[PDB]
Length: 253
Ligand SMILES: C[N+]1(CCCS(=O)(=O)[O-])CCCCC1
Image (cartoon, rainbow, N blue to C red; front, side, top):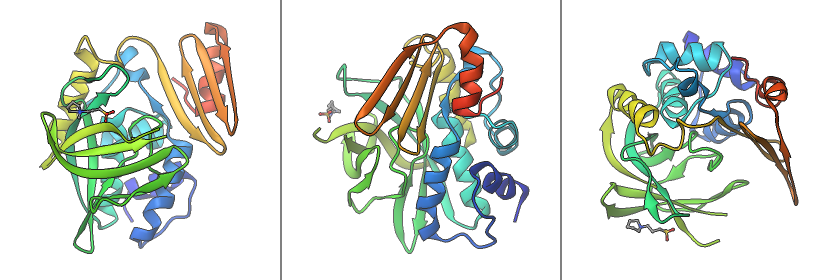
C-alpha cells in the first residue's frame, strides 16, 4: 500500500484495503463524490500547480480540497494505478447542450480502466454529473442518483467516443478520443481552463458536491441545496462564504 493509497482511503473515509477489486470501484466512486467536491478556487486564487501525483496528493488528499476534471480524474487515475489496475487518461471536450455548442477544446480529462479484457470509463470529475460507477464501453446504461449514463462509439469533431446522459432524453455530455494521453495533456487542459476566455471556470467561484440525499452548489452569490423533491436557493454574502465552504464542502483556503 503506497502513501497515495493510504491518504486516499483516509480522504474518502472508507476502509483501507491491500487488495482493491473491480466490484469495489463503484463504492469508492460514491465515497469520492461524497467527500471531494468539484471546485475551481485555485484558478481564482491563482495558486494552481502542475498536475502531478504529488501536487494532487497534497492539494486533494492532504489539504482536503477538491478540484476540476483535470485534477479529480487524474487523482483517481493514480489511486487506481497504485491499486494494480490497468488505467489510462484520455482527453476530450465537453458539450454545452443548453446552448448547443462545444465548450473549450480539450478541456476535459478522464480515466479509462481495463478489466477482464473490457473497457470502462472511470468518471469522477464531470461536475455533479457523476455515474458513481464505471461506465462500460459495451454500451450498457449506468443508473445513478445523478442521472443515466452510457457510452457510444461515435465520431464527432471532438473525439471518437461519447458519454451520453439523461436526468429527459439522451444528451451529449462530452466527446473524447480513446487514444491515451499523459499528465502533459492534463496540464494543457488546466492551462486551457485557466486561460481561455470562454472557459466556464475562470470567472466566478463554482463549488458543487453530491450529498447523502442530493447535492449542494455554491457560487459568489448563492447556495443551492437539492434534496429529494426539494430545492433551496439562497443568497450568500462574503461573510458567510468561508463558513459555507468549510461546513458544506470541507474547503478551507
Ligand atoms: C451531435 N452533436 C450533439 C447534439 C446534442 S444532444 O443534446 O442532442 O445530444 C451535435 C453537433 C455535432 C456533434 C454533437
